[PDB]
Amino acid sequence: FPEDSTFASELELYLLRTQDAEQTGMTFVHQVGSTSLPVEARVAKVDLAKA
Amino acid sequence: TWSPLAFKESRVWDEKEILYLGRLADEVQAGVINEQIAESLTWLMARMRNR
């Protein structure tokens, strides 16, 4: 435990957790001369923490 | 004949307020009571005027 110094009494650590949407998925297979089809919807999440 | 009157009062601050005193919005260090003493100083200045 290397020592450290501060001027204030209480110590608050606020952690911000982040689950970004993972770049997954393969490009859809189609035949030349066709209208394309769209991609799915993905989710990202943010949670926090107090200590 | 004539004889005056005397008017004195005290005001103290204990250790727990003079050490633990920040603010509400910010993460300010403990040196706030040195600013808050001046308020009671000028308040006793203005309170001796009211007698």
Image (cartoon, coloured by chain):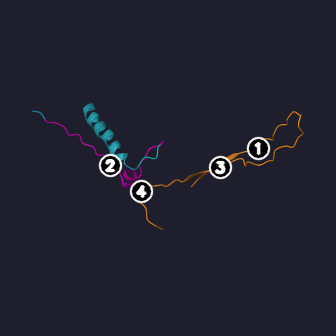
Q: Nearer the viewer, residue B19 or A26?
A: A26
| Residue found at the very far bottom of the displayed protein | A1
- In the rendered image, the quadrant that contains the N terminus of chain B is top left
For the record, the magenta segment spans: B3-25
Identify the residue shown where x is 42% and y is 53%. Answer: A8
x and y percentages locating residue A22 in the rendered image: 73, 49
If you read the primary sequence from the N terminus, does the residue marked by circle 1 or circle 3 appear first? 3
**Chain letter corresponding to the colour cyan:** B
Label number found at residue A18: 3
Asked if the residue at tag 3 contacts the one at tag 1, i.e. Cβ–Cβ closer than 8 Å, the answer is: no
Residue at image mark 2:
B12
Residue at image mark 4:
A6
Local crowd size for mark 3, using a 10 Å CA cut-off: few (<14), some (14–19), many (≥20):
few
Q: Nearer the viewer, residue B36 or A31?
A: A31
Identify the residue shown where x is 45% and y is 66%. Answer: A2
**Disc 3 marks which amino acid?**
Thr
Identify the residue shown where x is 88% and y is 37%. Answer: A32
